[PDB]
Amino acid sequence: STEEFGKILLKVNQDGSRVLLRDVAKIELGGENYDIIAEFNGQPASGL
Amino acid sequence: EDTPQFKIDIDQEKAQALGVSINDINTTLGAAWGGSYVNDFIDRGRVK
Amino acid sequence: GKKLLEAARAGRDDEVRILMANGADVNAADVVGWTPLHLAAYWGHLEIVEVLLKNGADVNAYDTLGSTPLHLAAHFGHLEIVEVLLKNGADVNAKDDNGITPLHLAANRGHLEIVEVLLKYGADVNAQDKFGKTAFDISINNGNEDLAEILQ
Amino acid sequence: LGTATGFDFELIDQAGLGHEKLTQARNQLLAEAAKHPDMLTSVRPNGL
Image (cartoon, rainbow over all chains, first blue to last red):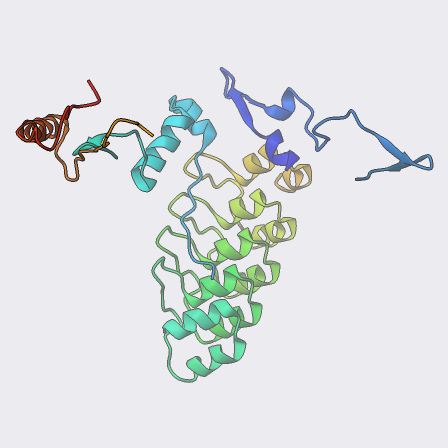
């Protein structure tokens, strides 16, 4: 889950303060790549 | 059928704090309790 | 005894009663120290959790790592069983060998209803585990904002 | 097709014997073969 990735611990600061992955990045499900986008009669689609 | 299993959670922060690598932890656990194929040797002329 | 452990896990209500009305030990334990109550709690068999408590099963029975049925019930979000257990005098602040409480476990999985009930029976919100963590500490780390303000 | 009269023989280590014992056995075979010029000629190792 994005939640679990978000709370990945990158480091602990001098003062016990914590740096999680969600503090340096946006985390979300998204395509392996974003190069292909299809439409069926103008409406959003996928296909094989 | 499902059976009881022994779940061990490694605490990332504690380990980071103590300065123990996660790789040393997993190799130590895995080698000790699962066994580790290190490399080959020659037993009476045959590679084993 | 062994047939009760099995029947408890299987959720076989009737069979639980048969072996009750036949003298099977309600506090029998398997290899990892789980009672029929542990099993019923884990697999969410409410009707068997009640029958067992009724026939006097130890409510604060712990396994070989110090975990109680309240731990299992709370962890896997079985709200009704958490209520039943607590009413039957389950130690709300019980710790396993890790210093982990039923509240730590409910919090981690974000079981708000269960977290409320536990608090309602006086769960110690300040209780720390072996790593010094509280239920609040957990809610913050998980980024659970709803749960994080319930714990203030 | 190997022409010649030609035979093509393989001596084999079937147990744990090792290169040195195999060589000794080979030498033993070659010395015996040499005692039958009537039947065998040019019985020699193909290797080094």
